[PDB]
Amino acid sequence: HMQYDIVAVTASAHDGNLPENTIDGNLSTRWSANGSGQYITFDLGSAKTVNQVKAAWYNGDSRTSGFSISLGSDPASLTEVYSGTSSGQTNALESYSFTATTARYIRITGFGNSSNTWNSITEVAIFHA
Ligand SMILES: O=C(O)C1=C[C@H](O)[C@H](O)[C@H](O[C@H]2[C@H](O)[C@H](O)[C@H](O)O[C@H]2C(=O)O)O1
Ligand SMILES: [Ca+2]
Ligand code: NA
């Protein structure tokens, strides 16, 4: 089981809850961006075999959040590998697994949540599981 370093994080938008808060190891710090279609992009630094993305959701034990995962070598031309809704049943890292493929960049696109239009993520980790 491999956990890859995330060398950089960017995002479409944020409200002062920075993108890099998703890789600080702290469930009390988050990235937040308001509105369906906002996204956050994780850079592995080079192309790696990836088959699993874990995300911990803000208020993750009290609301469900819609999202998709896309990956690839070109941020402008990523491929969607996963689409779903967070469980609403834990604040912990939740695993979203998919057929193994190569990627330098992993993007999470959020569609808001069952309470409001925000996309708020406390932690992300990216694996070859
Ligand atoms: O994910 C959130 O719910 C969230 C993220 C933002 O960082 C901010 O805290 C946001 O707050 C909104 C939200 O609707 C919340 O329910 C409450 O109404 O405050 C407003 C706000 O803009 O402060 O919540
Ligand atoms: Ca955090
Ligand atoms: Na925002």
Image (cartoon, rainbow, N blue to C red):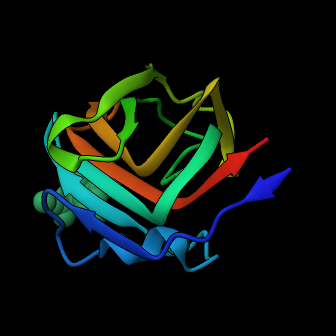
Instruction: Identify the residue at image location x=39%, y=76%.
Output: 20
Q: Is residue 70 above or below residue 21?
A: above
**Toward the viewer: 77 or 121?**
77
**Toward the viewer: 41 or 114?**
41
Q: Is residue 20 above or below residue 95?
A: below
76 with respect to 56 (left or right): left
Image-quadrant location for residue 40: bottom left
Q: Given the current orientation, which residue lies at the most extreme right position?
A: 1
Instruction: Identify the residue at image location x=44%, y=55%.
Output: 121
**Toward the viewer: 20 or 128?**
128
Q: x, y percentage for residue 79?
A: 32, 27
Image-quadrant location for residue 26: bottom right
Instruction: Identify the residue at image location x=13%, y=41%.
Output: 35
Q: Is residue 29 above or below residue 100?
A: below
Residue 54 in sight:
no
Q: x, y percentage for residue 101?
A: 56, 31
15 with respect to 20 (left or right): left
